[PDB]
Image: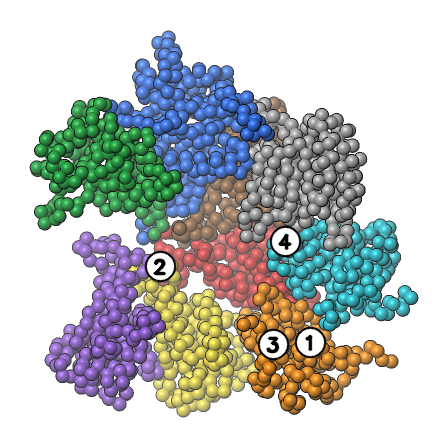
Chain colours: A yellow, B cyan, C brown, D red, E orange, F purple, H green, I blue
Amino acid sequence: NQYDTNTTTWSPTGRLFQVEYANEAVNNGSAAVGTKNKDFVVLTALKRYQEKVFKLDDHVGMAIAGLVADGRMLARFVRTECMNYRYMHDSDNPLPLIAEIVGEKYQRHIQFAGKRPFGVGLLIAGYDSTGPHLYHTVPSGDVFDFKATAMGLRSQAARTYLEKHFESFPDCGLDELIMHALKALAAATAELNIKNTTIAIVGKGTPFMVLTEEAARKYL
Amino acid sequence: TTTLGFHFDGGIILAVDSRASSGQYISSQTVMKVLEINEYLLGTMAGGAADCQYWERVLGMECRLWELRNNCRISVAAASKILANITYSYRNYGLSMGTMVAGWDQFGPSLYYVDDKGTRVKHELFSVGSGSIYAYGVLDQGYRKNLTVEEACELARRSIFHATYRDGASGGIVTVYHVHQGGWTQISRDDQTKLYDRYV
Amino acid sequence: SYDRAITVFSPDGHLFQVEYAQEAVRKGLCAVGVRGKDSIIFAVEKKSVQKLQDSRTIRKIYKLDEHIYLAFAGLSADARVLVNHAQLECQRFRLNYEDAVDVDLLVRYVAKVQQKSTQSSGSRPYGVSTIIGGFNENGQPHLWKTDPSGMSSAWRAVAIGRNDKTVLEFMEKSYQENMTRDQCVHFAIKALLEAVESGSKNIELVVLENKKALYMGDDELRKFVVEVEKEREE
Amino acid sequence: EYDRGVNTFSPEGRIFQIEYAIEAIKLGSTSLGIQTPDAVVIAAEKRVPSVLVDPSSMNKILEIDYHMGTVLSGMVADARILVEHARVEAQNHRFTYDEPMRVESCALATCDLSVRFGLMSRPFGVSLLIAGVDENGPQLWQTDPSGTYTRYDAQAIGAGAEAAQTVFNEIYHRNMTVEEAETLAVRILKQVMEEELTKSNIEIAIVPASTGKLEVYDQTKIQRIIDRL
Amino acid sequence: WSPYADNGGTIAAIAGKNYVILGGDTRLNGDFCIHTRDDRTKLFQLTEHTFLASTGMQADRLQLQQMLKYRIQWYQYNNGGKLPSTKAIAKLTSTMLYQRRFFPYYTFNMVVGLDEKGAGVCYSYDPVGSTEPFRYGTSGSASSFVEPLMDCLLTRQHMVELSMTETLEMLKNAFTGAAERDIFTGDAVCFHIITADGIRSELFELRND
Amino acid sequence: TEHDQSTDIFSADGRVFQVEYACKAVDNGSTAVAACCTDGVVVAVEKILTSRMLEEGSNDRIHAVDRQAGVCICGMLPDGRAVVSRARAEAENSRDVFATPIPGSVLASRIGEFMHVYTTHYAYRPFGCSVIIASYADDGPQLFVSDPSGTVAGYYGIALGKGKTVAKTELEKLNFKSITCDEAVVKLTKILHDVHDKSKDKLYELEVAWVCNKSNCVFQHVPNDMI
Amino acid sequence: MSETTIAFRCNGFVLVAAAGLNAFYYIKIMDTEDKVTQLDSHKVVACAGENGPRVNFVEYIKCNMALKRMREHGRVIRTSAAASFMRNALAGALRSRDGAYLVNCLLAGYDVAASSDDDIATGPHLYYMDYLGTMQEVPYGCHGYGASFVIAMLDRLWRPDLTAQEAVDLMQKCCDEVKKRVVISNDKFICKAVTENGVEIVNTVS
Amino acid sequence: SAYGLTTFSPSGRLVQIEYATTAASKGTTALGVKAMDGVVIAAEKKTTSPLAASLTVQKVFVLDDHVGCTYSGIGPDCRVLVDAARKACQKYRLTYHEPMPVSQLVRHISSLYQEFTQSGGVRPFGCSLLVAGADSQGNHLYQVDPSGTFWAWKATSIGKGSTDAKTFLEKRYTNEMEIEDAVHTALLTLKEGFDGTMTAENTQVGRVSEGKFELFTVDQLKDYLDQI
Amino acid sequence: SSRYDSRTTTFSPEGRLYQVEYAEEAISQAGTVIGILTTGGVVLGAEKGVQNSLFDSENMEDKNISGEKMYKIASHIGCSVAGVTSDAYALLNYARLSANRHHYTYQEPMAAEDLCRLLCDEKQLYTQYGGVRPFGVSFLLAGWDRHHGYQLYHTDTSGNYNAWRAYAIGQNDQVAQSLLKRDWKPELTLDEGIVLCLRVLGKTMDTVKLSAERLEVAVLHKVPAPATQKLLEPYGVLPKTVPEFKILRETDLKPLIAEADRQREAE
């Protein structure tokens, strides 16, 4: 295949091949799941001790899938954007604006020869003046706003489960929502417990937080 | 401030006071004017407190890297040089420093003075600071090469004491350190007012 | 400005630019170092005796400072660059620290110059190996070898360049602790003539002692080659 | 080799330069670390290329700071560069906040620098086990050319890796003593080495929770372990 | 036009075996005027055991407080979620002040907090960052009379353990006297008492003139 | 056939194939229609939904660039987005430096210039979107398209993407001298519903925006109660 | 000008001398600093001025000369080239950001034939220099507050054919005159001689 | 793109420099002749159609008051060198307050050509120059080629009809030609290789004499053409 | 564009820099150049191309600065080149400028080995860094300094250099070294050294009579020192003799082309 070495080469059917391959890096990381009700977002992730969930500011964090060194870069970047914002404004970086700028950073790495794609997907979960928000970012620079989804390996199954249940999630409380996020992450698999499964939460009243093994015992 | 150092047969003595004086108001009586750079080298600090502490901390960070890279302890010659070259490069930037560096490496006891312009002088007896002009008076009468360690600690203590008694910006507690082959040892701390009653 | 990536991995952990640099060292003339009690002996093979070549030949053993020599094998021009950087480094050190640089320190400086040339976009690796020997200020000799990858290591004796492996095998048997100055020369010459044809004027030789160095003449070097050509018939 | 660039992704989302660099580490000496509760132990095969080499000079164990040490595998000269960045970071920390760097932070810092290539022409062909004591007790972390870093109860890297990870899934329990790890170490070195095993031919270091200092074992004290076998 | 303004007022702290008490007045002064009687910028919390306390130019203390607040957030991200201890923040702060050697913060600062053994400490700084750990400290407009008084009552060097309560009363008395005599110090004092449990706060009125 | 790997290269026929291929992205993306009316401009796009669990407002193709101007990205969405940020900088530039809302013809010119430049350097690739520009500044209602080549053309009505050959046939039956913004919102929505392929893309919604005299010449999504 | 230096050249040598004193304002820190720095086997330089400019300057000369000698198989550089090198650096610094070296120098060398091919006039040369980069060959020269007194004695008593013993007597008298008439105390002098056989300290001159 | 385009091939050749040279040899004929008191250079300027304006086509160029040039091969490449040359002459004036000697100017052109054979991302200039001038050492005619090599000549020619032009000048050239009979010889040599009738509108001529370079106007050149 | 990169500075599978090698071939194709060391100076001789009636002189005011092949670098150093002419001119500027910088700094003439090293370092730089071809030149340097007397050097495309008593670069350099090898000896006058150079060129051009118009000769020798301006420089000292580089004209080659044809017939 002549058309699949660089990012700066279209193919005769209007495909960018190197970009689809970066996208496989995501389909082959460990599964993560997100879901949201009226006032919280829950991330869960199946650790395959590997940092897979990062806090980006008081009101927002993310799960990754794929190349971790890419995840860490995208984190230094968002953290520095939120801090800047709060220095200038004394309030929280709004979440739609976080998504835009991540999207654009990714896109620049798919259009020049001196930049490599990012081989890492994010589930960004946060909470601001317009409620909770769950964004998915992929290496093509696309940015979806979801009520629920899953990424990474076997994560189709997680996706199927969620598809039957998400309509009920607006009404759920924070405990059923966490359980739905686990039955989903389970569907992508050894079983879940406090040494290989992460849970994080953010919402009204609730700065972004990874549950400790104690608090997580209740759910697991 | 007063600090002195000198070299004798058993090693080196450093002694200081602990007062920090804008010029009228006395901000502290408890400054530690000897800086344990590590466990074979001492600095002293006179002039600007922030300057001396930042740059001797930097010096101490270079003495440690040297010893990671080379598997051995840096000499007193080179330590004083690292510090003289920093002061030299900052010559035009208004630093205020008058340091002694003392150590016992393979060639024996070494005492250097190093200042804010990049001076670096090696010699057997030094005193630095506002009260130096009284310390030297007492120190030149009593000093010789063959002092015992006890006699030499007394000489240094009496010298700083006499400076605190007459200099407005020296005072507080008098501290004496001894640099020996094995490293160094804090020998004493005595409030200068309690020393007044010992020596009268 | 040229920024291409020259030295890269290929499908089994091979850096080919580094390998081929080490090939270039294998074709270069043989050099040997031998550490005695209190003397280091560097001995190198010269191209070939000619009527026309200048009697005062150019030296292929360089001084880095009053107490540290270098011999090499490989691309002679690359090595001259390397020797320049090392002479600068020693003088820089005197200026920053007053004391004279330690051999072991100077070796890590050089070796890191080689390593960087294996990772710096725009540039190929040097094609040189070095043998560096010198004293501490406590009078104890050290002999180091550096290779194109940037890896350094200390030796009691060592050969590089062409017929490296053969000379090195001879030297594994025959080496002896606490050899004298004269024994060290003997043993070094011997070691060389396992790769080299004759021993008339295709050998230069430094005897690096504490507080002295000598680029041996042709009277004293003929004396030793005949003491050694007489021993090779037994 | 030049047909595809330094950045290219494979059709299954690996970066070629990084796969090949990991292969490089496999052709390395073998090295390993084991975590007890009391202490954390590291060791390596030396592998000199003759008996004219002074063995001192070929260390695969390096002190980063008083409370942590590394053992490297893969390209030694590349490791020198990482071990220097880590020494500098550990001392910047103490400069700025007057206390020892955590071991995890040190592994994090060494991994940032791994992935700065596109700038450097290529990855580092190196993996590191960092071992030390901070407040979380004895720790052992491993970094690799991808820039992933990871905590391990016991690992090995190098040519004898895959064989040492079947002496682990057998004999390794979490709850062992200093002694049993110092012996399990040498058991695995004997196995996957090519040479006969000797006190000059291997290196061992410990960081015990008792004192929080790395100690490097003499040849006198490595005799005592081959003896106990 | 100078880049420098001194907005006035006073802070003071006292430590004991498992607590520290920290006070700052709430007046913000202009040139021959008063901007407000209810500024609370002098004291700024950094962790649950560590405060910064500052006098001098208020715009500078607000910058320094933010630079510290983000170095501290960065430490946490690079350190597994942990917070730096009081001793570390104090060393961090010195380091940072020195670094503006050449155009300095016009601030007289204190870092005040519990140590690792659970005991109070106070670090007083000069504007370029030389400090030491001490049992008490004060800075600002009234500090040249509050400080001999604390020297007197706590060390008693020219004579022949306190509760939280006795210590809070001594400080209340010391601010009351400062407000009577220092024309730039007044209105109220905000007091924070730091224990391992947490932080108790208490406003306290002072002369309004 | 090495002539088609960089866009810095003509082919022997005078073509630039990297630019043709990028145009093929656009032609296989989703269908958008627009109409320049008496009182303003209307755009409508069809979002193909990749998932029933997307929040509404996800992967919006229409963005505001200035109080009075907006773009509809057709083709690859993130490429389109980089074009939106440049368009806003231009619009901001005109207010900052020249005190004027950018004219629609000028904004389209500057977008074209921008897309053109990624057609000439070995190190970059053409964009894989076309951008519909809808404006209503002091020059009146304007509708322009820029494409990956950087060609810019003004239109009364237009259609891009896979449905575009039928949609064009229906846009020809309108009357562009009479039609208002209110009538157009109805007619364009009917055309997107008819050219929609039901076998291939089961989940879609319509996005629709406008800049008219009603909206006080502000570019904005139409209120959702008008479809 | 608190530190006097002195030098003069005779038929087969140069004597150089410099006052030991190092002072902090009015305080004498020490009176035995050797300021007559050897640059090579047949060169010395006496510098006057503060410790810091003075040390940094002569260390920079030494290292650049040392680097010129290995990039040249240990061949000794002529005195007039060492002076030309010193002069270019004083002059350069004077128009630089960091500004001038405030040092005043006397450079003394004895030039000796490199090889047999070498046609060089072999003998002693003295060069006066100033912190600006002025440079001038001279038969004798001085710097510091003691300079005027000594220059006149030497105008009065110096000849080219003084024996080594007479030239030490004359150097001694010049040091005494400085002590007698300069208020700054230059109490102890170190004096070195540069000859065909190299640099050597002169002990009887104090 | 910062890599070299011009490289050595196994037998030591630099082929991009030979292809460039090939292009300078396929250009319209130009020639030069050095007399005892002046120099004359001349060139064909045929247009492709009579729709083109003849008068605006330049083949001979003034570089400064005392020196001029002409070229063969790729016109547009020649403008780069003419611009560089013109600047270097003014630069020399500002510095020394006298006219740059022709030998110096030609070494400047050379080193510019030579740059474009080693520099990264560039091809060589595909043109050769004749340069004609007068300085304190007299009158000069030089040729410079895409390699950056230059030679002084008494008489020469470059471009497609140049082996024959040079043959013809071997025979008719003498060391004691006057400037008016050098113009005659110049024109007479152009006439032989020239396709079609040669006019004052498809030929251009320059002349150094009395230390001054000057193009002939069309009218001056009609005078010399009715005489031959 | 990176696929059209030639990779000029990249080792190839045997530790060989092809562009360094091909550039050395280019020198072997070039006109013959010979250097000979004698007791009274160095001699450089070079063959020239074939002499067209229509060539002309530059008519330079000074004739001892450059022929077709010989160049002055400074008053104690000259050279001859073989290989890409324009490449030689770039390096000769480099060397002239370095020699004069050294005079600027030390007010003394640069040693010929020091000069040679700077030249060769410049060459080596295009072999390691920079994505462009190397210089395709070889030089012979004739030098005089007080460290080492007369010196003759050769510089090769690799950035290597070596000293010689006689040498030959260009076309028929094996045939030429064969002859010098036989007939060189350590006791030559400068007039014999010139003869020997002419014979060696006569036997590589392949002619019985030496055409004086096909030869260039230059000599680096010493001559008595000019005026001593003791009034304008009272501490000036000049040696008895100073080096000169001289590009012998036809009027000095007449008794020397005659003595090479009496040694050609008596053989």
Q: Amino acid at mark 3?
A: Asp
Task: Residue I45: give x, y in percent of width and height.
Answer: 39, 23
Determine which residue is flagged by label 3.
Answer: E6
Q: Are marks 1 and 2 on the same chain?
A: no
- Chain for mark 3? E
Label 2 residue SS:
loop
Viewer-side residue, D180 vs C167: C167
Residue B88, label in figure: 4
Task: Residue E121: give x, y in percent of width and height.
Answer: 70, 76
* G196 left or right, relative to I20: right
Task: Residue G149: give x, y in percent of width and height.
Answer: 73, 39
Determine which residue is flagged by label 2.
Answer: A113
Q: Disc 3 to disc 1, how far (Cα)?
A: 23 Å
Whether residues under marks 2 and 3 lie with C-beta atoms below 8 angstroms apart, the answer is no
User: Going 40% across and 51% down the picture, which residue do you hit?
Assistant: C1
Q: Disc 2 to disc 4, how far (Cα)?
A: 46 Å
| Mark 3 crowdedness (10 Å alpha carbons): few <14, some 14-19, many ≥20 | some
Viewer-side residue, G153 vs A174: G153
User: Going 60% across and 25% down the picture, which residue do you hit?
Assistant: G121
Q: Disc 2 to disc 3, how far (Cα)?
A: 54 Å
- Chain for mark 1? E
User: Going 54% across and 55% down the picture, which residue do you hit?
Assistant: D81
| Mark 4 crowdedness (10 Å alpha carbons): few <14, some 14-19, many ≥20 | many
Label 1 residue SS:
strand
Determine which residue is flagged by label 1.
Answer: E122
